[PDB]
Amino acid sequence: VPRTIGAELMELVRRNTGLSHELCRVAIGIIVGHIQASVPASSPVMEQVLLSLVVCHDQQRLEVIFADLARSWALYEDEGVIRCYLEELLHILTDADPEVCKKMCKRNEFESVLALVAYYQMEHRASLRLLLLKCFGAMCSLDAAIISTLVSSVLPVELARDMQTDTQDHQKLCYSALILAMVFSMGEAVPYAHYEHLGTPFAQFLLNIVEDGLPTEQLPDLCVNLLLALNLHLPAADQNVIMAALSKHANVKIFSEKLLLLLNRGDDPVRIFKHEPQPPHSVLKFLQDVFGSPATAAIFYHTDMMALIDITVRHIADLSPGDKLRMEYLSLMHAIVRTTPYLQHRHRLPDLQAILRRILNEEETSPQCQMDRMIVREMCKE
């Protein structure tokens, strides 16, 4: 059995059946496997073919598509043609070999990707823009370097501007919000050239969508998650654009409640992909920034304050020692007692004292419990 039977079979079935990568592997496994099963004494070859499983059509098609779309000439053609182009691009980025797509997108210093962005800036046909957004989302699922490239490019700027411009397009608005929530889910780079396009005004816009809404209701929570993605890598207290937007207008109860729910769930809505050096928790960091200053801490009403306190203390007392979340919740409490009148109400405090006493008396030899220990010892201020 040839040492490269696997990739050869994969390529052949791919090109001649139009099947997907995974489904090609599955088909090969089915045929070879059942042949091995039914016809005994055929196992030596079949098992080797199966072991082998563990230029191409897709590569050259990516070459042709990326080259043609970078020619913009695509603005002076029939919408159906470009539609087929972007459809094929999407299908390739979704169903072909991941390594091929990674290799092709990163060619000539991401020339193809950047050309696709520069093209997206000029294309105003909604269908083509939608397809382009989908393709970008497909690229984000490949590698984090492409995310860094896109967040370094002019794409987020054009997305924000398009969002504030074409508000009467719910679908493209949802997808734009999603792509934006994806490119800002890395938290790697901050270009202040985009801050001139995505500042406190854009934050006020998103918050206005969250609070008031548009004339399905699947754009409000996506705007929330977008605010989470944006505030993932912003400043701390006084130089934060979103926190500035919250400082200007603190009459946001719906958003605060949404944050209370998101904190109650515990899960991160911004953590979508699995890349190296994972970023911080969105909701926790957001609430930390909220209680990094009283003015932003005002967004939680008298009721929502006690509620949030209860949920936080609950998470602290429920999280076992060694968890990488308990430290963040303890930090949030330490910020809440420093930004809010916690001593005035003293709600959920008798249990909090027992929680601190139990946490400090933890004989855990772990480093995480140690960090939680120094944090808690710092929080012990009379």
Image: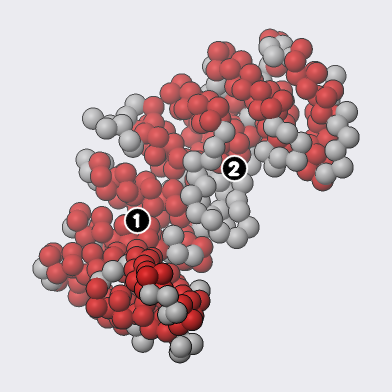
Left or right position of 343 against 96: right
The quarter of the picture where the C terminus appears is: top right
Q: For this rendering, which residue is in front, 75 or 241?
A: 75
Q: Is residue 187 left or right of residue 253?
A: right
Looking at the picture, tell me which residue is in the foreground, 242 or 127.
127
What is the x, y in percent for residue 113?
Answer: 38, 70
Find residue 128 and report its horizontal and vertical position in percent.
21, 60
Kindly identify which numbered label has been placed on residue 158: 1
Residue located beneath label 2 in the image: 281
Identified by mark 1, the residue type is Glu
Q: Secondary structure at mark 2?
A: loop
Q: Residue at x 46, y 45 (%)?
A: 199
Q: Are marks 1 and 2 in contact (CB under 8 Å)?
A: no
- Who is closer to the viewer here, 2 or 186? 2
Q: Looking at the image, is mark 1 or mark 2 earlier in the sequence? A: 1
- Callout 2 amino acid: His
Q: What is the count of numbered marks?
A: 2
Residue 20 relative to residue 259: left or right: left
Residue 183: x and y, percent? 45, 55
Residue at the spot 53% in from the left edge and 30% down from the top edge: 265
Dividing the picture into quarters, in which one does residue 358 lie?
top right
